[PDB]
Amino acid sequence: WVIPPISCPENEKGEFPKNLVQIKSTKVFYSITGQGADKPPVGVFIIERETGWLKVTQPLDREAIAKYILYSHAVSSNGEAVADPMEIVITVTDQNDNRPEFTQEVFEGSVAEGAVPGTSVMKVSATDADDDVNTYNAAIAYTIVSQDPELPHKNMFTVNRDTGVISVLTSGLDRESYPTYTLVVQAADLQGEGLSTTAKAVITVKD
Amino acid sequence: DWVIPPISCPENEKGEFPKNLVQIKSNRETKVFYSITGQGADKPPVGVFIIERETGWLKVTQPLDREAIAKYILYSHAVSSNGEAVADPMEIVITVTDQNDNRPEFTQEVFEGSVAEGAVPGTSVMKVSATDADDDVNTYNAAIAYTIVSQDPELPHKNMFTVNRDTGVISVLTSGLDRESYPTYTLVVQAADLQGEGLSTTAKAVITVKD
Ligand SMILES: [Ca+2]
Ligand SMILES: [Ca+2]
Ligand SMILES: [Ca+2]
Ligand SMILES: [Ca+2]
Ligand SMILES: [Ca+2]
Ligand SMILES: [Ca+2]
């Protein structure tokens, strides 16, 4: 045989089917087997019997299947396999089509009112379904969007953009005055420059 | 003949470099040395692509940028240890595939428009436009949807105007324009790719109410 590495981007558009590669091996008839061919999901990839042109029949979702393993078969017209089945690996390449997702809707934390600026309070966390191995499409930066109340100061807390750890930023926390803060926290991919989602951190001020 | 399949590589890849692409081969029989020529190999940008001289493994050495170069045209060479080419150079085409790494940008910071006060709801006012440097032929990464983010003043109500999400045409949505109370509106308009769901930017549309 001879089998090149094969790639298809997810979320393609336009006319289908789309040509991938021509598989070459008495007239020969080409077949593919495997999950994605004759097994679920059935018919995502096909091959032309006579030409050996391997094709994709629909847009792909990498977050469903990121890698397909198929086998090509070559059968003469008289009915004999003229070659061993050849392993074909198709790599589905990533597009940034998933926003980060916070693991909780409302994270809860507490802080001692006398805690010095720079004191760690709590941690927020988010996942991103996109390709964190080969891309930055899942590279999350955390930021604080808003603080309620805006008292005594507007920015009482800060979040570490890599780790999602929230710390005391400035002085002035006081249980008697404002016992609770609701922060809107954001997670944004492409290292903060990309798609984003929000959630809340509720911080209660202790003695 | 040579054997050369389609080669593609996504832009903006991270991780360890270099990365394997495909193995280049010829059926010839002495010890063969492989090499590559072209822009991206031995010509500017030099060394983006390299080949292992004895194995024929073609590799990329760094992240690519489709908006700089979307397609490379290289040639592979096969030379015996005695110094004679043992095949004719083979064209190798490398397609750089798109990532959504460009946010849309409006063609102006402030678009200016104007509307007669008694214009019936549904009347076209002005147009906003944005472009996107990503691949609009093959992806949704440059597929812009227009929306109105905000209207100032919010009087006599909000939603005085609307925007066609495909065309950027701003029209009168509801009645109530009154130049002697609210002489102008500043709309914050957004263009967002992936059909409205993706990367976004904002601009202003300032509308002067005529009589
Ligand atoms: Ca997907
Ligand atoms: Ca993502
Ligand atoms: Ca994806
Ligand atoms: Ca780019
Ligand atoms: Ca874009
Ligand atoms: Ca791009």
Image (cartoon, coloured by chain):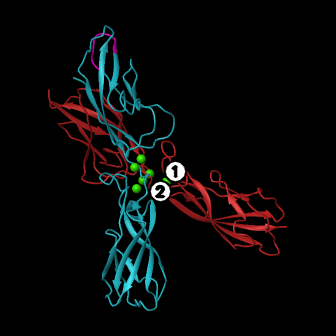
Chain colours: A red, B cyan
Residues A45 and A178: in front is A178
Q: Main secondary structure of the magenta part?
A: loop
Residues B109 and A137: in front is B109
- Residue matched to label 2: A98
- The answer to whether residue A67 is seen in the rendering is no
Chain containing the residue with disc 2: A
Up/down of A169 relative to A148, above or below: above
Residue at (29% x, 48% y) in the render: A43
- Residue matched to label 1: A138
The response on whether ligand 2 sits within 8 Å of label 2 is: yes
Check if residue B81 falls in the magenta segment: no
Query: For the residue marked with disc 2, what is the amino acid?
Result: Asn
Q: Which residues are magenta?
A: B26-32
Query: Residue B32 falls in which quadrant of the image?
Result: top left
- The answer to whether residue B160 is seen in the rendering is yes
Q: Badge 2, how many Cα within 10 Å: few under 14, some, many 20+?
A: some
Residue A158 falls left or right of residue A105: right
